[PDB]
Length: 304
Length: 304
Ligand SMILES: NC[C@]1(C(=O)Nc2cncc3ccccc23)CCOc2ccc(Cl)cc21
Ligand SMILES: NC[C@]1(C(=O)Nc2cncc3ccccc23)CCOc2ccc(Cl)cc21
Image (cartoon, chains in turn red, blue):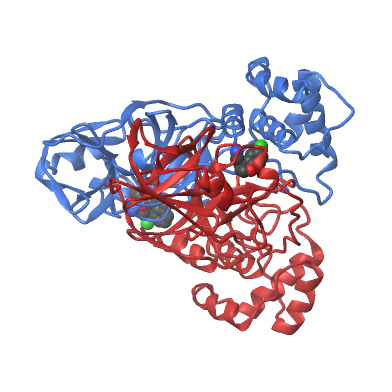
């Protein structure tokens, strides 16, 4: 019993973190095999960030201008290239701690763990989600760039995020491990405002199923609804539309609890319309949307 | 910017987890040097849990009855002893991944990370706190016993908790690494009810300081108070009394924000009396109490 915002064990990722310095700029890099991946803005000064021409700034950089340190030992850079918004620094030594890994580009609503790092050293691990507006609500200070987001399937780490930027609103933007930003964000210190941060409906429903599995059942109502009627309410509350694909994904949670997906939608509809009335669900006074249906099944089943 | 419920990187602890089996009972153990620590209830059947006489049950167990597996390799048990509610299984091999470590007994209100494990394998990491009633609100399923709670000071892991039990209310009880339970709980399947789960006032105040540092300032009021007046309100709301020691501990957060501790107390007093009015603080609709003042300084400063 109990339900926590749980991150994946971070050991496999801690073994990959290195410090990357270019001139007077330092950030984190991810060392997998003989390649260190890091944000390309490691080549920028604070002034360059205002309007950087990365290809031009990179002409002034050679392999020896990128200092890669793993622990307290220096790695030898034998090649470098820019792929979208990341640099790939080829080193002469394969990371002996390289786990089984994949690079994946996640969809909005998908969750992942972040290992926040400073100077190549891990400081903490937390769970977050790719928001529907393609920002993430992380916890990052200056120097955290290059920290990564990931999921683990038994022994394989699927890297899905690399931290690059903080918007003026305190939310975060980054790329997948091929250097493509999530959403419309750019690695330039310019006016970039995020769109509506809508609530991830399928994740709220999954967390309401977790609440029923853990004994919090007060919100279960006597009603049902349809996807169309539910979505009319979801639109009004800035919740993402629920599709039949989301209903299919919630199937196993529906079977475990015996609560039909549309009945849970009707319970969610009443919670949106009536509020919580000072009550809590799994220790929260708001509807939590950063647990996917897969996360709920994993946490409630004990997948290692 | 941003403020997350952040756990310590779990790698150093993942390297210590092993599976311990005694007969048909399996749980997790912690392998440090040449000793594996685990809950003594690994010797019990489901029936024994109702009224176990551990000393008597242990007479029927020899070193070869405790199966310790690290990964997919078996460790040789050369000694065993019971210390309070834990068994210490001496093995012939020192854990090569033993980090620098200490065993500490924490006070209520103190936070720590938990590495939830099943069959000696890590499944997730989350942050929690020792409640004022000496329970913890974890996320544990059957088989999670022996999972540990810890804090990290740079390279030294201070182990503070080992999971043993779930109360009928879904909250958790466990011991320090010397086998002494936190609070009045026992490793027996009997009527054990938790006391009042009061709110950890000093931690709420620390989290209100984190909110001000991160830009959430709406709740800052035009008032101040005294410890005595504040505590009259705290008592009414089942909040722990605030002492001058808590005020001293909040000193650095007071200096960083320029908000006197008693002014923040007055703001907290108004939030308790008026409610949130549908507003949020750091993405929460309730007052968060599982961040200590040290956690806030660490997260807002970037300690690795
Ligand atoms: N140091 C490089 C960089 C960075 O780390 N950004 C940040 C990323 N995340 C959280 C931050 C929290 C406070 C401060 C900066 C943060 C990225 C490139 O553009 C900039 C531009 C300005 C500044 Cl002051 C920093 C940066
Ligand atoms: N298997 C041993 C043990 C255990 O793991 N307990 C649990 C601890 N934490 C979370 C649990 C969530 C569901 C179930 C049990 C949980 C501890 C000893 O006493 C008992 C007694 C009964 C049962 Cl059914 C299990 C146990």
